[PDB]
Length: 93
Length: 97
Image (cartoon, rainbow over all chains, first blue to last red; front, side, top):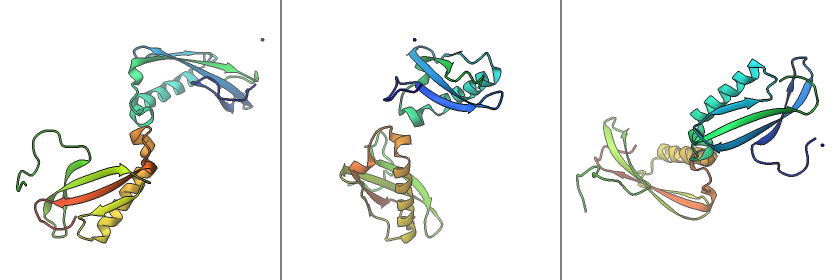
């Protein structure tokens, strides 16, 4: 057992960014959503505090601006687990 | 009909609201905005504006913002498939808003 055709499972995306070494790298982010209390779980972040805090600010904005995007879905009623998988062994994002 | 009873107690029907504005004479006045929504092509129709050109420009600006921000508000309702008519009712007779 990089990006297959067709829509992947929802919550799964690919982002690109310069690594700690400045080289571009492609990472795939996977989100699992269950019924919960708005908890945020993180994994695969290369234990990097910067990415952890970036995701924290993002989820803060998501809670603050949920009604504009979701059209009524409550973020606080679901728990989210987000994981990072590097596709090109370039380095941490 | 009524007369006085400016804002009745209880829930109004959807599309009807009340605002307060500075008319052409500068004295604050109450107005009622009534929106009639039917199946259509997103066309906007106006009535009760005292033929004020600035008021019609305001209506056009508001409907343009509604079209640009339909997704951020309705979350799936299509404005392009429904026509709206806005009627302005002046309940204190201060002047056009």
